Image: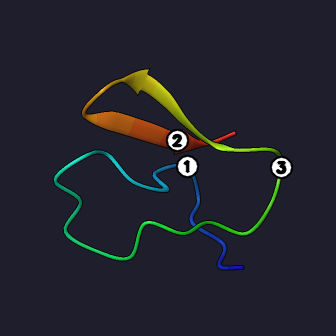
Amino acid sequence: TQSHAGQCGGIGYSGPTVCASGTTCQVLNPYYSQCL
């Protein structure tokens, strides 16, 4: 559980994909996933 301020991922992510809480690591476009 880690506090990624917005960008949890984005497919091709230069770092660890795992946020803290909310509900999900949610898709906007396939290449942009956000901490929602």
Please say if 24 is above or below 20.
Answer: above
Instruction: Point out the tag, 2 or 1, that comes first from the N-terminus.
Output: 1
Disc number lying in front (3 or 1): 3
Q: Are marks 2 and 1 in contact (CB under 8 Å)?
A: yes
Report the residue that reaches farthest toward the right. Answer: 22
Mark 1 secondary-structure assignment: loop
Cα separation between marks 2 and 1: 5 Å
Q: Amino acid at mark 3?
A: Gly
Label 2: state its secondary structure: strand
Q: Position of residue 27 (x, y in %)?
A: 47, 29
Which numbered dot is residue 6? 1
- Name the image quarter holding the C terminus: top right
| Between discs 3 and 1, the one toward the N terminus | 1
Residue drawn 57% across the image and 66% down it: 4
The residue where tag 2 is placed is 34
Residue 22: mark in rendering: 3
Residue 31 location (% of width, % of height): 24, 34
How far, Cα to Cα, is label 3 from label 1?
Answer: 11 Å
Q: Position of residue 5 (x, y in %)?
A: 59, 59
The image quarter containing residue 20 is: bottom right
Residue 30 shown left or right of residue 35 in the figure: left
